[PDB]
Image (cartoon, coloured by chain):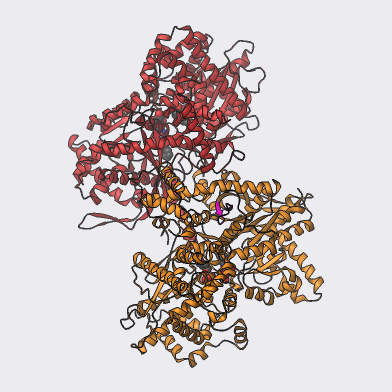
Chain colours: A red, B orange
Amino acid sequence: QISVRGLAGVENVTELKKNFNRHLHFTLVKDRNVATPRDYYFALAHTVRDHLVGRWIRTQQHYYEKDPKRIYYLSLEFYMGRTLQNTMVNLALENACDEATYQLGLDMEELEEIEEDAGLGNGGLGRLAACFLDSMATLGLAAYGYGIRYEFGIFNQKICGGWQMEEADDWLRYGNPWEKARPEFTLPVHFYGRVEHTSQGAKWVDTQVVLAMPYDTPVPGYRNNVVNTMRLWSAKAPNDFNLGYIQAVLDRNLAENISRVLYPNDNFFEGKELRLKQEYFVVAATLQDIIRRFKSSTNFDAFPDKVAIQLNDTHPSLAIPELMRVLVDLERLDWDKAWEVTVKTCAYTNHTVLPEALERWPVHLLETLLPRHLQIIYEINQRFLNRVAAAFPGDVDRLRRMSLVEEGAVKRINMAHLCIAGSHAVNGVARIHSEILKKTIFKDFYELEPHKFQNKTNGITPRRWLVLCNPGLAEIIAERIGEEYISDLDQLRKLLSYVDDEAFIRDVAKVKQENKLKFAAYLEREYKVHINPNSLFDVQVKRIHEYKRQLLNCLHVITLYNRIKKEPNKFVVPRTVMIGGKAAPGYHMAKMIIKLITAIGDVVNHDPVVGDRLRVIFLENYRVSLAEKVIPAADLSEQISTAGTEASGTGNMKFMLNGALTIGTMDGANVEMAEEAGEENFFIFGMRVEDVDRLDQRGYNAQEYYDRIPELRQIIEQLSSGFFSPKQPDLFKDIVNMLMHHDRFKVFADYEEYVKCQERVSALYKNPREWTRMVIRNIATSGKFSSDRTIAQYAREIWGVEPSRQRLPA
Amino acid sequence: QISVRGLAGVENVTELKKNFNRHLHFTLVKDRNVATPRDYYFALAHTVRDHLVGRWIRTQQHYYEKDPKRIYYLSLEFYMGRTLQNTMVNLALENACDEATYQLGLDMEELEEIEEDAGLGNGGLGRLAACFLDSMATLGLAAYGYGIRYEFGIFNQKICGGWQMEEADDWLRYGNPWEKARPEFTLPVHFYGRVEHTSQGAKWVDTQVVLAMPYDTPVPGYRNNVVNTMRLWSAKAPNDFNLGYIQAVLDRNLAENISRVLYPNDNFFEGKELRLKQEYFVVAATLQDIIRRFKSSTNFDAFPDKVAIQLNDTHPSLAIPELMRVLVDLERLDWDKAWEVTVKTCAYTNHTVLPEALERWPVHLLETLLPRHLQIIYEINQRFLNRVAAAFPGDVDRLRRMSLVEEGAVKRINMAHLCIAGSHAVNGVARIHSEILKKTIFKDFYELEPHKFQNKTNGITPRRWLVLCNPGLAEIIAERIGEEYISDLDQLRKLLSYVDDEAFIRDVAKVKQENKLKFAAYLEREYKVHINPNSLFDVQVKRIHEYKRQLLNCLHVITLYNRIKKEPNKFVVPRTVMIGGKAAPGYHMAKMIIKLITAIGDVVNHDPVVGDRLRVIFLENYRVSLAEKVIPAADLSEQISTAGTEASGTGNMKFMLNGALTIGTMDGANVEMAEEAGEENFFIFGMRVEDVDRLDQRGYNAQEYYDRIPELRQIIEQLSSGFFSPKQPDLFKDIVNMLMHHDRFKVFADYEEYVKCQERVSALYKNPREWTRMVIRNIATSGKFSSDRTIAQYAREIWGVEPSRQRLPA
Ligand SMILES: OC[C@H]1O[C@@H](c2nnc(-c3ccc(-c4ccccc4)cc3)[nH]2)[C@H](O)[C@@H](O)[C@@H]1O
Ligand SMILES: OC[C@H]1O[C@@H](c2nnc(-c3ccc(-c4ccccc4)cc3)[nH]2)[C@H](O)[C@@H](O)[C@@H]1O
Ligand SMILES: *Cc1c(COP(=O)(O)O)cnc(C)c1O
Ligand SMILES: *Cc1c(COP(=O)(O)O)cnc(C)c1O
């Protein structure tokens, strides 16, 4: 049908049809009389998977023969989403499969909707890991993703009476055709026990054993015949575990609980023992696998020449003391040599500066669970502080600030300090964030070892986030500049030559309009909600958090409502304001924000004076599959975190690539997006980082803004008085109290500038030709935000390997 | 190679090789450089499974079109063993697969050894269910086996220091290629709650829900292209289950524990709540499935014309009140009509008279767990006792004896009484057992409803228990009388014509000798034990229980030892005495018996004066796969239960078919085996049932036997004094005390006759020609003990359906 989806040759289509019928009969054990749409989805998935296998085997054979340096990306989260369409895109099978299924009387898009998201992450950090895997395969790197196979991923969100309810995400219920269990590479992981010191070094004894069983998932590169591996570990009890009899068998669940469920926090740390077990479990199994693969090519001097370990935040930070344990206790290397190898092997990426997100584990937990690792951590600390004292003699306060061990009521280990000490490279995830790291929280470390500190601005894969989710846009671009941009996104700059082209302007606006109609129809059928598809689609989708300031958006929505009610017969640009995202189950204020958003919708959407001029919709169960639908439909992207809080953002980049304009603060990657597009082509507002600092120095007083801005005072009085909660008048008093007295994120301080900037958005939307010209300038300059660029920088500047765009044989 | 294994045609072999390589590559994702023997096993299993699929689909389609009466065999146990070889046998693929694998450089017998037993039963009852499934498919019956998919089957037995240790049987660890999950036919099962009485009848409300997810396994008939289904239910929590957040997800294990583990008792009842949940779980899911299938052809008058439900003991007895619940509470039938339908639909097989094996559930458990079922049980009881009172007016004691409700400290429901009341047929499992039921424990019921009581003597499948495990014997029989006997075992009578044939005598003895050599080599390699393969192989394999009298065998072994020590230079016929079987984990005396057997071996096997004249071997981890190896190797089958205690036995029949002679009491099916072969061709000894009764009337005094038999006194003094436990002299005092003062099974009363009868065995073994002639007379008359005969009788006399030997199209 469309060119970027590849060829539908008669021979390919015939073969796909034959294998589909083979899998329906032999694999699923159905005939066409009893088969459901789900059976048809599975038959297609097995058909497509068969095309990966030869390439997967050949890729792994190739790495064995060439023995390149191997890159191990360790993460507690991989937010993969669906795999069927992405696999077809990367193997150039999409049109052939569409034709094959059409000839069998089936609609492939309907079959795609059956697949569950692999929701093994919370949001941006887990999704970044998924984009990175895609880019590493596309760049021909010998890369392995290692994590945990959670039985239950991020919870499914239901809204009941306007409140979030959580339900278990039983994503494996129908089976996962993409994974292959490898019970033959099962490895032991140790917990508890105690340390004995013999004359032959330290020995960790009397431990409890849990088995780590790997499941492998293929990761195809873009049309290069490279298929890399994501290896996820699942916890299994040994067979003599606890071995009255019946209870001993039932108690196997205690060991197997390690891989049961993803902790559903975003930017928040809880010191729970089960989470620490998860972190060690991934690290211990992974490092044994790495070492086994290294030995099958003891001279550990070459280890950092053949192995790079990238730590995705501090979550796998125990890799540092585990690597030391193995090298010193088991391989019998002297400490100094082991440390040299460790530092050269490991690199650490930081993803947040919020103090409540930083992992600081109580010493008593580590002492009980991982007594040998605690001893190694203390020794690391003592040697590290000896270096600090030599470089800054007499600076006693610096020693306290830089210690891996934090003193207090409860002694804790600062895992970020451990990662810096034990890594040859430390990076932030956008330029402003990397600078903030060097100037504030890691300033002392930067002064000691400036060479370690780098920036690697985040990116997104253009396969999933353009070609897959927005084929209409991909096609009209390809008609002008060919297909090479899909793996070389900088080529989108060529579109600046079409900014005055009437045909291109029309085609860009036509694609957006089609995407909006499609999304409006999706809403009506799956959620019984009607929207005006001529309205401006104003979209804020991301996890619910005070720092992301969904509350600032709520204040703007109420402002627009109140202005309409004041002058009902004045023209205003119609908007559909859509907000979605999950709240962590224990985060009360985040749950209250969801309730406020739905309560505003309840009033606004049923006021006959408003008409279809303003609609407020809470998008339920925001996840990767929903992002693929709503992002192509958006006109305005809301990226409105308080300056200094969003380390990068990646949703921002997805919206830019898909033809939305951005309203945002100078935070995270927004800064770089504005720099690339030109500030004139971005809706920038609000305090910069320096302005936030100045306000903190004199003290933030929310009352001053309340006193000076009548429109703001009216909103607070409405919230307090029960205007949005007539049955429960005090329902929102905690929100009001936080905004007035305890607001860490300064919502009121950016209110005036935000509202004025929103008026400019509305003014531009009235002139569709100029709106679309600005859009073209954004899409055209989005090339920097390809994860292929990000990964090439990690490869050259951290890992010491060269990317390749060369194809392996087919 | 051998004819009974079928044809190896060039085209078939070529196709098998091609599909094996396809599964290795696409299904297992291996190449031949990295593949292990386990990978080769899986590639073969998937290759063979593909040949079942077409037949499975076509069989189920055929039943849909013809709509025959359907037979539902409900069991808490299906002891299936391995499936690969049995599937090849039933599809006539064995020689083709052997040739195909040989050409690929692989040994098929080595691949067969990799497969795990499906150990979803304890012993004879579960194995009977498996033989029955095989026979029902071979006889073309529209039959379904329904049970539970236990995650852990019967424990693996290890012997450590001569003691049984148990380890979990993690049989699903590597996957099960034979099953197909059917998550689409998942059904709800209810627990707890309470009963409300409206004007619109009773309603069971406020229940906890567990989901029952079915897994289907094919059951192929013998060369008839029929493939029936075994459907096993697995427990799953609903997704809103308990829905802080993390704990709620972890607590899903509480619901899923229902299908976690098989209770490992044989002939012993424990009133544990988890076991009651298992029993209801199977019944509730199964009955909904049955009713759904019946509606897809509400006139329940035809239900018993289209449905038969066979209850395998009382374990699924809740089917009776559940069927009543559904018909009365949900379908709104009047009680009397519902009861008529229930009784005509259900039939009950009793498998034991031991009082400690009978299920008697406390009323307080049923009241809490299944409050509506308890109400229905009381109503059944009141109506049943009203009939008893009308038939036997004034017989107040009969009313108490026959009640479903037993009075006492704790009120209980007698489940056997419930099954009799609610079934149109009640059967025992061998003639003597069926007679004992009518004369003793169910005498009152027999007097009320004599027409209900039947016998169905047990049987074994000759596919698994001759063709599969003993191909050499199958072949030499087939050379003389053709292949029809495999599905018509009565044709073995034709072998009586070859009792004087010197060639046949030689061939029978040659096959036994080959089987013995093969087993002796198996012992040496897997267990480091050396045996004399010219010795008489004296074998007792079955679960360890006081009623089975492994202790009587131990006394004979010690007697032989003591006689050798007394006259070391006298000739005695050499024996290898092999005893194996599992003890239930809580059954102390059974565990002590295992220890005694290994302790006797420790003394006997290392005494240089004994030489290779006597060896005592405990066979570890006795299970279906081990039975297939040892039974073909046996010379003497020990079937020595106290008369009146072994309801039938089925091991006895396996030994008879495979060319062992039997030493046994007149118990269970032994009676009928002796009748078929002639008493002159059996080694019968000991008390008959009537003699046991006479001894009970005057009182069993073990001291009398001790006082009168010097050889017996010597053994007891050796046990007591620490002769067999020199480091722990009192180790066996509980065994001695039980034998002398508390022996319910009268071991001493049969000692003298047993020893004398064993001397006659030895005398005959010295004359190999006459030994083999007697063997031929046993094999030749074993035809009655085919489970095909048993199933044909159930079909005609209970279920009301006609067996068919006709082939479905290929
Ligand atoms: O670089 C990718 C993205 O990482 C996000 C992040 N930064 N920290 C986390 C984070 C922290 C903790 C946990 C967590 C989860 C479970 C248990 C404990 C901690 C999850 C995510 N996520 C940042 O907020 C984004 O600005 C950034 O674009
Ligand atoms: O007909 C097939 C076989 O059934 C056996 C049996 N009779 N009862 C049981 C039995 C009873 C209870 C349980 C049980 C298991 C777990 C939990 C509770 C009870 C298991 C088996 N097994 C008899 O002992 C054999 O003589 C007979 O050949
Ligand atoms: C990209 C993405 C995120 C991250 O969005 P931000 O706006 O950068 O927080 C979160 N969740 C999902 C499902 C995503 O696809
Ligand atoms: C046949 C069989 C049994 C039953 O043997 P009995 O001697 O009748 O108790 C028990 N276990 C296994 C593994 C069997 O094959």
- Residue B98 located left or right of residue B545: left
Query: Is A211 drawn above or below residue A97 in the view shown?
Result: below
Verify whether residue B222 appears in magenta.
yes
* Residue A351 seen by the camera: yes
Give the tally of numbered discs: 0
Query: Magenta stretch?
Result: B217-230
Residue closest to the eye, A619 or A39: A39
Residue at the far bottom in the pictured view: B708
Query: Is A556 drawn above or below residue B56 in the view shown?
Result: above
Query: Is A290 drawn above or below residue B305 in the view shown?
Result: above
Residue closest to the eye, B368 or B755: B755
Q: Quadrant of ligand 1?
A: top left
Residue in view at x 59 percent, y 52 percent: B226
Q: Specify the quadrant that holds the C terminus of chain A.
A: top left
**Residue A471 x %, y %:** 48, 22
Residue closest to the eye, A92 or A541: A92
Q: Quadrant of residue A356?
A: top left
- Residue A386 located left or right of residue B328: left
**Residue B93 x %, y %:** 48, 53
**Residue A98 x %, y %:** 51, 27
**Residue B352 x %, y %:** 60, 71
Residue closest to the eye, B557 or A699: B557
Verify whether residue A344 appears in magenta.
no
* Residue B191 seen by the camera: no
